[PDB]
Image: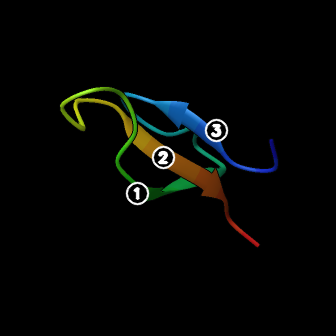
Amino acid sequence: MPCSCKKYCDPWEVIDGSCGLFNSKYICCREK
């Protein structure tokens, strides 16, 4: 996956959506 599901992003990555079941997690994709 180019993107990645995490509760919070990386110092080099930024949010892009909401993953998980009740959207609890976030679809964080690379800062490009």
How far, Cα to Cα, is label 2 from label 1? 4 Å
x then y, percent, for residue 32: 77, 73
x then y, percent, for residue 8: 39, 34
Q: How is the image coloured?
A: rainbow
Residue 30 lies left or right of residue 23; in this view the side is: right
* 17 to 7, vertically: above or below: below
The quadrant where residue 24 appears: top left
Give the residue pinned by disc 3.
Answer: 4
Which residue sits at x=28%, y=26%?
Answer: 21
Give the residue pinned by disc 1.
Answer: 17
Classed neighbour count for the residue bearing mark 3: other residues with Cα under 10 Å, few (<14), some (14–19), many (≥20) = some
Q: Residue furthest front?
A: 21
Query: Which SS class for mark 3?
Result: strand
Q: State yes or no: discs 2 and 1 in contact (Cβ < 8 Å).
A: yes
Give the residue pinned by disc 2.
Answer: 27
How far, Cα to Cα, is label 1 from label 3? 10 Å
Q: State yes or no: discs 3 and 2 in contact (Cβ < 8 Å).
A: yes
Q: Amino acid at mark 1?
A: Gly
Q: Amino acid at mark 3?
A: Ser
* 32 to 19, vertically: above or below: below
Query: Which SS class for mark 1?
Result: strand
Classed neighbour count for the residue bearing mark 2: other residues with Cα under 10 Å, few (<14), some (14–19), many (≥20) = some
In the foreground, 9 or 1: 1
Query: Which SS class for mark 2?
Result: strand
Q: Earlier in the sequence, mark 1 or mark 3?
A: 3
Which residue sits at x=24%, y=38%?
Answer: 23
Q: Earlier in the sequence, mark 3 or mark 2?
A: 3
